[PDB]
Amino acid sequence: GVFTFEDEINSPVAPATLYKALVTDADNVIPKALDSFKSVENVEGNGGPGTIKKITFLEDGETKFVLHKIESIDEANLGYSYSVVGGAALPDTAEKITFDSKLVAGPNGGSAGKLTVKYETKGDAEPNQDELKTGKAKADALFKAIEAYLLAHPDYN
Image (cartoon, rainbow, N blue to C red; front, side):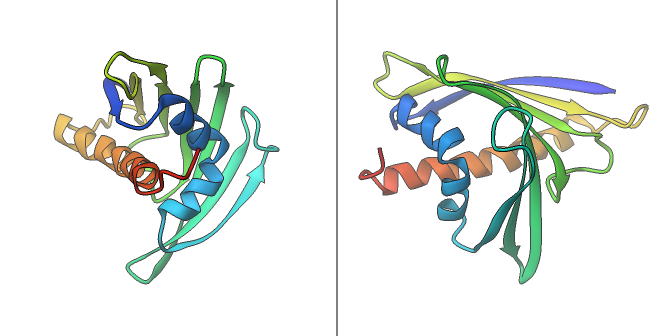
């Protein structure tokens, strides 16, 4: 029915700069991180907590889009909550996926925080452990894109 996985996050980029560019520059990073960024628009919400944003990207010459929702923003603790409700990032065997990532300064000299992935299933149907791994690899694919941008663009604060 519902599965919850916890993962760790590590990045050589400052946690305060990555968090701001992650939620604050999220709409600005998505287009810069996605070389083929087509366009982005908000279907509902003004960008605050619970807002719904729609992003469009070009893949395999096919126009695709993704929908993301926010449950709450916590800049003070550098942490926020978001989940996908539409787009190719929405599996049919899973009702919806929630993502809870936090950001805290660490002694490593970079950014650190805990990541929590929530996988919901229609009901009896449930993805095997391997299938769940591919689901997480999809999200990590986006983080690396944003993280690679910060490392490739040191002028970004």
